[PDB]
Image (cartoon, helix red, strand yellow):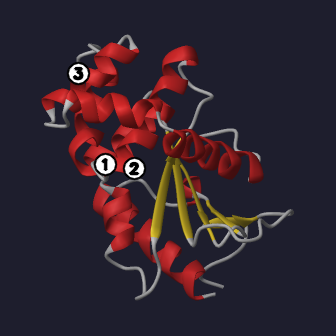
Amino acid sequence: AQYEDGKQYTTLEKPVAGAPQVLEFFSFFCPHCYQFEEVLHISDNVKKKLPEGVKMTKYHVNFMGGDLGKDLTQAWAVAMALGVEDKVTVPLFEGVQKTQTIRSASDIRDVFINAGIKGEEYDAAWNSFVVKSLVAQQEKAAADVQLRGVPAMFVNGKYQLNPQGMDTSNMDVFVQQYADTVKYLSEK
């Protein structure tokens, strides 16, 4: 057929109940994730093709970058709690991978300050139980799909995108294939 299990996607042997509809995992340490966000704009192109009533979720993961990787997962929780994802995603990617000016939790915080989040506001969120639970949600979701690599995307806790099974000749074409595949799975 056109879409085949094992070609553009794989099926989870052990489906995850109550999972987010579209669930993306990434790391600010992950070089392909940098590509996905900055060069390919994958999350954004998936969004534009999702049927009405399908929300998109993006979580950070711990298993890259050791101690900083965990700080980054908590900071992403801060970004989700404050609703400032779209203001910090690029400076965080660039601070970790481009300029390499993010080496500590303080440097992470600086990115938020520079993006206009107030210090007191950042620190209150950073230390909050709401952020603690948002960290736990991110960790639970990755654990539930036994996640070992990023970037990764899951549809309804049953399907896993399989980007290697798509031509990378043309960046634009890859992005639309990925997005159409998500839509197909979505409607399944």
| Residue holding disc 2 | 80
Residue 177 percent coordinates (x, y): 43, 70
| Residue holding disc 3 | 110
Separation of residues labelled 1 and 3 (CA atoms): 15 Å
Identified at 65% across, 73% down, the residue is: 156
Viewer-side residue, 149 vs 108: 108
Q: Amino acid at mark 3?
A: Asp
**Which quadrant is the C terminus positioned in?**
bottom right
- Provide the secondary structure element on which disc 1 rests: helix
Separation of residues labelled 1 and 2 (CA atoms): 6 Å
Residue 140 against residue 156 in the figure, above or below: above
> Would you identify the image quadrant in which residue 16 lies?
bottom right
Q: Earlier in the sequence, mark 2 or mark 3?
A: 2
> Would you identify the image quadrant in which residue 42 lies?
bottom left
Q: Could you classify mark 2 by the number of other residues whose Cα lies within 10 Å: few (under 14), some (14-19), or many (20 or more)?
A: some
Q: Amino acid at mark 2?
A: Met
Viewer-side residue, 62 vs 172: 62
